[PDB]
């Protein structure tokens, strides 16, 4: 007759839910009969159907509790605590491995009998992405290594190029591939600290569309983004720990996460450039655009900016020995799944269509 | 022992989709008095009241004696907020719009029903006026809805541009109500931008109303910082990466910023920002639209032409049932029949004619 | 043995008290014996004498409570909840009607045997005000219609004119007549949202003495008031709901209230002028000035700036039919009272004195 | 059957944990059976394996508590209280000695049969660092003396030089060697006090990469860092106590900690220079760069920027007599360990390789 | 019983004048261990500890098991702050100074006693060096004290002005400690200005350290807003009307701002601001003072010349017993006798001579 706080926490931990309202909403859905539950029968959400039955009894009681929010708060704090421990005790490679396993879990479902994704359309995204930059699978691989090694002053990559050249598309994919947050430093430096606070315990960070000053010649608006980053050298450096605040108060002193900076060809101060271990210049390509025009599903289903598309790319191009030993078995399994559905020629055909700019699946 | 049921208050909040603690408190306290001698119920007036007073009388009676009224309402409101959060993350955007349409249809059943106070004839007149605001108006609205539903990266915002009193706000307000969402003001100092932007959390779409730019001294347009601010929010408009929205002195949600509309006078738009606008609609003042209104005061007095319900009526009247979500098609059919029963093509065409003539829409 | 929270709430509701400290102070007065209470017998304050005896028992216990503030907070929240429901469920005319009934209650007392107001001095105020603008009673009537109708983009009146021309006097009187708040937008926009939040659930708002820039010619100091208003087009239009915040405890998305803007002949951008349905230009008048010099009570007793003076004006000049059906019976009573105390010539004599610049009651 | 708050506090005290989420996370790991706990048997984390068995019983109960965060807060407050007492009552040498003992504790594990660190790779770091500046071990020794003596207006050292000259590398190592915080004063003054509040109860502080002006000729971006420092003369002097704040959390009036300032050779006002007892000019050296290119582990494992590398350097170079009496015996043990691991010539070869610009362990 | 005594904790805080919740928490937790073989008590390291461990052992043992440790300490600290508030409003300014002197003398009794670590000879050397910093130094200090005690409207602030390293901070810090008070920094933006000012609540005096002005760019002096900020705080320096000091998101106290000192380099001072300064002392660098220190490092290493105890020792050595408050006089006489037996006039004069010669003060 008493709610089990521990069970709510268990559910939060199992789904890695660190959103109090989301947790509250999800758990309240379990208060209803699992025997007569359509959400479970239709297998709509794993975070729901894989847990409804076990949590039914506790949820029924939870529904009558007067401290619902408080209970969920402790549950979420436990998830945050776990993330804090992992950030301090796991190797960065282990962190990425956990991320990859979560993505593979989503893949098993989305490409399984209860999924609505078409593996063929996703491989088409892999094809398009592999035409965006030279040796794309190596670019992605080298990025992962850079993020994992997290070497002082060799932690950031710069994505520079004209409008609609693919900077955000790839940055977004990489961000989802590794896990992390996108930060906006173009806003006033007043609320800057709080924006930077979002990076606490994150694997990596992406400073999106940072604006500079000298660029009115190229019809580029001026902003303080670049000046702001140049005032954050100890953040990009990753040598000394910085002081992040995320709760209207100082919450954590830590090495700032490594990451990416994307921008529109503004001038970059040498002091800031020294923080970028690699710079990639993106170039708009007619065929990529024309291909997208006839391959609308790549944007509508958000495939080319997905970390899942990048993960598939790695599974298709990279040798098993490069992946963490603990996950290799699972990788081999997906390599076999892919070979059984896409011959080399078929994939080559997709890339061909991209270069020709004529519908990837044509 | 006569203990108030928190679960019952929560159920009431859920059924009325009440996410306002004070509103919830005020409403529940009304169920405190006898259901028998209640003018509110017998005279109808408010569904959120008469459809629940009897069922909640007993619990409300106890609630009236509680020393934790606000706390109880808080948990009820949090449950409603939690449901909104789950839906924003788990429903398809089409399902979201469909839920919104069903809510509007519920209001329409009442307002145009026995206990209602609306005159369908006056609302259809609103449809007529709106159809003369832009070319192929019903297609403009349909295309807008698909854009909002598809939520395609960097192809999610429509720009409404034009002179004072050309219809930008009228249509934006109507679409905002049709889909559900919030209107944000980014003309205010960025020192409070995050707080305004935070209002977008869990919203279907957003409207950046009357954004001011620079270099507008030509058309006597006062300069402002709204355009510069939007250009600093490219990741918000793009909808590719999740943004960090703050609420209550604390970041409460990392999410893809909602798609939407930007309305503005004729200021210059930087290339970087223009790239985030999939479509631009140029609004133009029309004497006959003005003259028609002067003789059709009820359209403004009853807030009909700026209403999402007028647009829903338009969609029902013009679009094929097949274009609507499968789950609400039969409901759309009942309305098409209701409308066909109420108005012949001639009666409606006369309304559009009067509008084009700058005369009172009716008669 | 224990205090009845509901009783404190009933007192708050009956007195429409939404000020926690005022409520606390008032209820504590009821803890004393009422038998020989002079506040009661001399009927000094209705908020006191109509309730002391009834609340004595509960107040005596309240005085020994350890949660006085908390009890009154729930009471005030109930009052605020009622205002919230009313703002969303009553027609705007019903809102105005409720306000008029509250003013009439105050009038019943003021001009009653236990009141200290002289109805003749107040009618003198009506006379003076009726000489401030042409067809004043119609101006007030039209203003009320404008506020009730609350038509999109046709909701604000602009009071413009030189120093001491009567702008504030009339705006203050109208504010009290309808109920609402006066907002100062001449201060930094940084703390502007705070001020805008006071408009939550208000019937109308008055932006007092807004300063512009083009005014060197008239020795008028520059300010940001006009630019600030111009950044609030969606607030003035009243088409879409805006987002108001009343500190970290009461946010609200609602249509901004309609109202008034008063200013000193500064330049007004065409974009801002488009939000004003009517502009009234006030002019200083020597006789109005000379009259007041000889009718000091009009200022000392704050009569010409009172909503009660305007309500008396409407009662004297307007046809019963123009008032809401439910209040007409009461308006008739007051029309009879005014006719009993003032013949047409006696009232006309006050207007004569005003026009001639002499003591209104000469 | 009720959780022991004192035991959680003891665990926090033993691990010197002043991070509520970290504490919560670590203590929750103890709720699981330890009998066959691999984290324990494999001895992966001292903070875990040295306490799991002892805290299992209390932790199993804690897991069922509804006040987990509150329990952890009292525990963390105790750790913060202990640090506050220590900062006010211990001599600065005792503070440093306590830090050295904590570092030595980590060293016992790192280089132990259970550790993962290779003493050879760490001594290679000592060799590289010893080539960074002339008489490096004396530079570190003198720095320690300056920090311990904490002499008014003779407590800050300025590291100045071009990009990638070793300023941050050495400052980061000295910061970890002594314990303290790295502060960023390049950001706006708004949250300047927030950043400065981080210095509360810290042994020393490092103002990293302070931006100045008048450096356009050097292609150095302008900033307000130097200007900000010049407005903090009372902080740098350490004569009067200053007032530090951590929001509505922890406030404190204390003498500001002594420390380091690193910068890119901008101009320094005489007023500011007067607060720097010593200025070290760093210079890029081709061989140091070449050596690192062939000794990547020094950066990948963050060895040259480590306080442990510096402590090993002091142990190797400095006479036992210079260390605090209470720690001398432990220093002797380490000097014996090092002498056993490396002969004078074997260590000299490492320095030889660095000077030659080749792999340190080549 | 099994319950902690909050009253005892408060008593401990009151006796140690502890207004730091964390320090109080840390200190009381030390009493939970057996007093029997406590090393801290036998070694007589900290009075705040060894003089109370035995008495509080029992209560502390129970306190160690409490779940409301911080709450208990907060009530104790609040009591200390309440006492401070009462004293600020009800004691004469002389009594305030007297209580401060008595506290310093208590510290002197220990530091110069059998369990102390201070060398009276080294501190007397500090008096010697300081007496060489300005003409008639003992009279300067005396006059300063009278100015602070009298607290006369618009005659409450002294201005210390001079070049770098001339002794401004050295003397200001010593006087600050001698009288008790706070040092404020007004060179930082006025955003957090109200917060720094709040630090002066209930303080005897305030020191505005190193205030930067405009101009003076002719003497390599970086310009700042310090002076402009002080000129905007005229009602604070005047001390005629009460000002409103904020502390923790709210103006926690309306009071006469305390009197004090302002130190600065050679920047220009507006006449409006100069009018709040009753006395201006111009400090000047002296080679011999510098050379003396180079050969008397302990004066800086042990923070002697910047100490309030050095100035109290100076007053004791130079000032007539009659100048001290009646209540402390007998105590002052004891110290005068202690000093005379420790140092003959020629021995002290020799110290001043050495300073003047730029040689080690001692020997
Ligand atoms: N190299 C490319 N060539 C042609 N079209 C591209 C290329 N990359 C992306 N696109 C197209 O442009 C869209 C947006 O790309 P994206 O957001 O990555 O650009 P950036 O991030 O390249 O540009 P911006 O500076 O405006 O942020 C994609 O949705 C796609 O249709
Ligand atoms: N195309 C039009 N032609 C003539 N009158 C119009 C038109 N559109 C709207 N109006 C009239 O002008 C009023 C204001 O319209 P609306 O708020 O939509 O304009 P905008 O939003 O067009 O202009 P603004 O730039 O001032 O915000 C309407 O209430 C209506 O009376
Ligand atoms: N039309 C008028 N003619 C002469 N005197 C007037 C007039 N109107 C108001 N006054 C005088 O001015 C006072 C009120 O002015 P307010 O109504 O305060 O002026 P504004 O609001 O007219 O001027 P301001 O621009 O300074 O705010 C009255 O108390 C009265 O003495
Ligand atoms: N004296 C040196 N000579 C050659 N290379 C060096 C030297 N010092 C450091 N480096 C190399 O440069 C990198 C960065 O050094 P560090 O962060 O200490 O420089 P700063 O702190 O010297 O420069 P910045 O002003 O950019 O912060 C090191 O990781 C190393 O590879
Ligand atoms: N009059 C003096 N002549 C020579 N040296 C002095 C004098 N006063 C102080 N010093 C020396 O200079 C140091 C700093 O003095 P202090 O902090 O008081 O100067 P200011 O406060 O005089 O200068 P600043 O403007 O830099 O704060 C002392 O520690 C001491 O070594
Ligand atoms: Mg982009
Ligand atoms: Mg508009
Ligand atoms: Mg006025
Ligand atoms: Mg550096
Ligand atoms: Mg100084
Ligand atoms: Zn289910
Ligand atoms: Zn009812
Ligand atoms: Zn009474
Ligand atoms: Zn274990
Ligand atoms: Zn002891």
Image: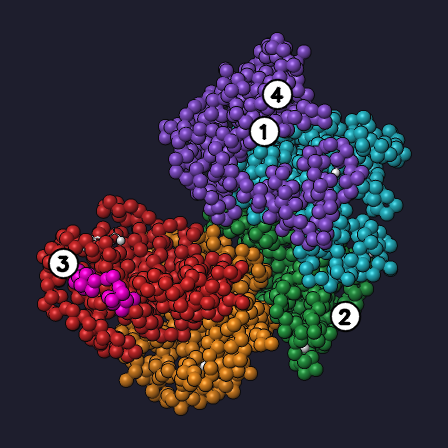
Chain colours: A green, B orange, C red, D cyan, E purple
Mark 4 → mark 1, Cα distance in angstroms: 13 Å
The answer to whether marks 1 and 3 sit on the same chain is no
**Residue C114 is one of the magenta-drawn residues:** yes
Q: Which of marks 4 and 1 is nearer the N terminus?
A: 1
Point out the image quarter for the C terminus of chain A. Answer: bottom right
Boundaries of the magenta span? C106-130
The chain letter under disc 1 is E
For mark 4, what is the residue?
Answer: E334
Q: State whether residue A165 appears in this view.
A: no
Mark 3 → mark 4, Cα distance in angstroms: 84 Å
Q: Which of C167 and A85 is in front in this view?
A: C167
Q: Against C271, is A218 above or below? A: above
Graded by Cα atoms within 10 Å as few (under 14), some (14 to 19) or many (20 or more), the crowding at tag 3 reads many
For discs 4 and 1, the disc positioned in front in the rendered view: 4
The answer to whether marks 2 and 1 sit on the same chain is no
Residue B358 horizontal/vertical position (percent): 27, 76
For mark 1, what is the residue?
Answer: E102
Residue D288 horizontal/vertical position (percent): 73, 34
At mark 2, the secondary structure is helix
The chain letter under disc 2 is A
Mark 2 → mark 3, Cα distance in angstroms: 99 Å
Mark 2 → mark 1, Cα distance in angstroms: 86 Å
């Amino acid at each position: 007759k008493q709610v089990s706080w521990k069970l709510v926490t268990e559910y939060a931990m199992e789904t890695k839910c660190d959103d109090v309202l989301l947790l509250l909403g999800m758990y309240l859905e379990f208060q209803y009969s699992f025997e007569m539950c359509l959400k479970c029968i239709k297998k709509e959400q794993p975070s729901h159907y894989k847990y409804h039955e076990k949590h039914y009894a506790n949820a029924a009681i939870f529904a009558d509790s007067k401290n619902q929010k408080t209970i969920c708060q402790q549950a979420v704090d436990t998830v945050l605590a776990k993330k804090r421990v992992d950030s301090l005790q796991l190797t960065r490679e282990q962190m990425l491995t956990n991320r990859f396993n979560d993505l593979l879990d989503r893949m098993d479902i989305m490409f399984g009998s209860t999924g609505s994704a078409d593996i063929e359309e996703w491989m088409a995204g892999v094809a398009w992405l592999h035409c965006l930059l030279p040796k794309m699978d190596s670019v992605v691989y080298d990025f992962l290594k850079c993020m994992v090694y997290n070497i002082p002053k060799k932690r950031y990559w710069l994505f520079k190029g004209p409008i609609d050249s693919g900077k955000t598309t790839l940055a977004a994919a990489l961000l989802e591939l590794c896990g992390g947050k996108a930060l906006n430093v173009n806003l006033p430096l007043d609320r800057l600290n709080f924006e930077l606070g979002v990076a606490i315990d994150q694997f990596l960070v992406v400073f999106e569309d940072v604006k500079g000053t000298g660029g009115e010649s190229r019809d580029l608006p001026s902003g303080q983004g670049i000046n702001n980053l140049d005032n954050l050298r100890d953040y990009l450096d990753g040598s000394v720990k910085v002081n992040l605040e995320k709760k209207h108060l100082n919450k954590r002193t830590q090495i700032f996460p490594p990451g990416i900076v994307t921008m529109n060809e503004y001038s970059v101060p040498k002091t800031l450039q020294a923080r970028f271990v690699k710079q990639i210049d993106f170039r708009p390509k007619d065929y990529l655009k024309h291909c997208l025009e006839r391959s609308e599903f790549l944007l509508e289903k958000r495939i080319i900016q997905s970390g899942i598309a990048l993960l598939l790319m790695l599974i298709w191009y990279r040798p098993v020995a490069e992946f963490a030993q603990s996950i290799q078995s699972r990788i081999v399994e997906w390599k076999e799944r892919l070979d059984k559905e896409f011959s080399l020629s078929v994939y080559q055909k997709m890339k061909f269509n991209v270069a020709m700019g004529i519908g990837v699946l044509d």
